[PDB]
Image (tube, rainbow over all chains, first blue to last red; front, side, top):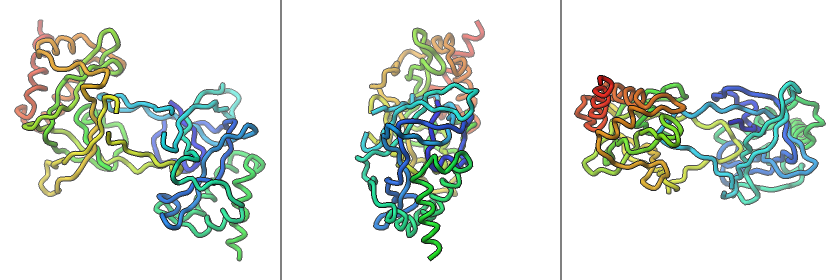
Length: 176
Length: 176
């Protein structure tokens, strides 16, 4: 099966994937409304990471990865499509390359119901919080930069108003 | 986290593991009571694969694998310890090497409640069914041989009465 990576997976490429395609999905928008206490932040001082939200006019550029078929032959691992703030569903992924027809992919999403969801907030604020945060995975700012730098390698900044704006405010903070 | 492989994982080594240790666990016994329709058998002509059953006098030799920390920084993947015929729990794993202290490991088990559970049966029968079966993964007999040959590389045949007996009956069938 193929899964869509709208975040860290884009650049955190050290995992096993049979194949990958740059592309985009629809009807969702990428927002930094997901709190991070185990990666780019910690409890008591959470960081912000991305999640996808339903947006009819929405688009999200990212990368689709083909997971290797599982080795354990004794149990049937399953997919639960429902589940406690994290959603699993599928959506159409459009490859950047027109040579490939669009195909279904798995989407793993953290909902408004997940415990870590921080929700929408003024960008001024999100940027600062990101500025300050650091977690087991690294600093919050590095996460944003990679993503942003990461997306730019694939599309014009117009593609993600929210992400690039954030990057810019942060860079400004880094100034003063 | 570390997971215990009592089956195919022992020899199907083409996956990513940070580390591995030969060892054994207790209070469970390995039996060929699990039906296979997606690996070593198919619907309408199922094969047999191993599952672990609670056995107070029981022991299971196998290998423990250290899974790599997950790359996705956006969602919290969880462990559900309860779940529809497959159980997830932990048990003590004793390394063959005394230099290492015993440690907890994850055990993923298919219960009597799973749909594919075929249950106990006369060994004469299981061997034949295995003889005949083939699935997406390969023939049923190859699965048994690898396991058996696989275990022997780690312990005397006395360790697994059930597995080696089965191997032998099968080899006999292969004769006539």
